[PDB]
Image 1 (tube, rainbow, N blue to C red):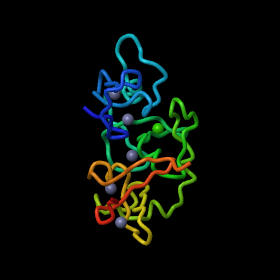
Image 2: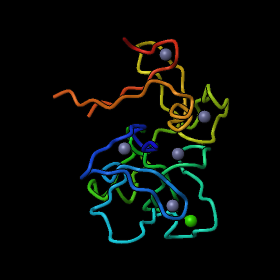
Image 3: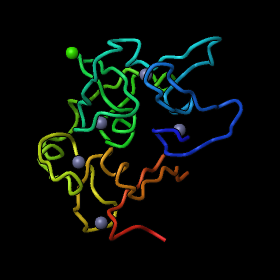
Image 4: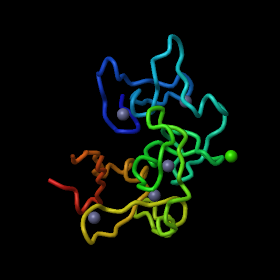
Length: 167
Ligand SMILES: [Ca+2]
Ligand SMILES: [Zn+2]
Ligand SMILES: [Zn+2]
Ligand SMILES: [Zn+2]
Ligand SMILES: [Zn+2]
Ligand SMILES: [Zn+2]
């Protein structure tokens, strides 16, 4: 079982993988922004609010995974928020609400995702390789198993198309 935000499976005992009691969402306490482990059942933000209906991500066309509410009446994947450079979290410990979506350039919405082939159905990011303009939705890149790594150089997030997967 694996955290659906960082795609890693941690046997960590303090920063554990929580399972939503209702939708079986799997996420690292620290990846989803959970202050502490509760005694009893844990519910993700989606299952706390409309447990029966699926929500849309404001930033992509995919429907599974870990969601938070935005500050403007919508929902968004934590991973989409993490990877689209203009998007923010108002609280960076609770990782919510997702905000600054209005700061995304319109250009991101005019790109075509090469994985799902859709244009205008989300905000695309692009291959980190210089002069590669191949674009993809964050969750499409994730689902397709593209290389996507987060590394702070003195946080730097780098995603690549399958041509430019790095050494
Ligand atoms: Ca709404
Ligand atoms: Zn994680
Ligand atoms: Zn849930
Ligand atoms: Zn999304
Ligand atoms: Zn896509
Ligand atoms: Zn590329």
